[PDB]
Length: 158
Image (cartoon, rainbow, N blue to C red; front, side):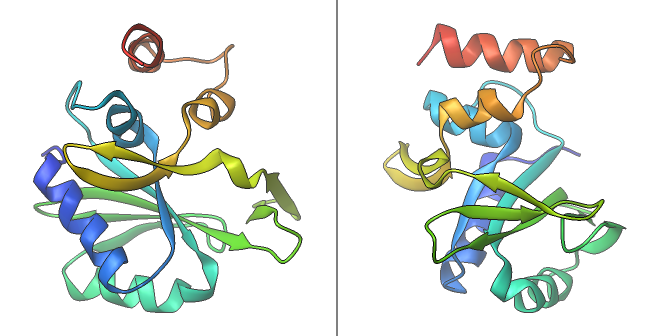
């Protein structure tokens, strides 16, 4: 019921073969920064180019993901019987150089371009948010025990 590394790679391969610009995020993004898997993962987080929103969703449905939560254009959660949960987040690659995301209650979140980078993971180049970005997106007041584990891993290993 968890997302295996090979299953992660398949989802990554989908976006890459679609030629849709994307970055790995969330828990799997953290492990990928460390260089190896650290724990079991319920879900995958992917930030992707919002201009391909319709193409991405249609493709995810084609392979059997069902839409469970739909807060678009900010965020959508899908569910696959085998591959598990996938959260996708449309991001805008803007002309000003900024990367933005729809704010569910009216407006845009503003992110810096350098938060979204790439790292080597088992001889594979994986686009993912930086270590600094993971920390920024975490709230130092409201961490789960797993969040604490993940953050200590980013510190203890990297």
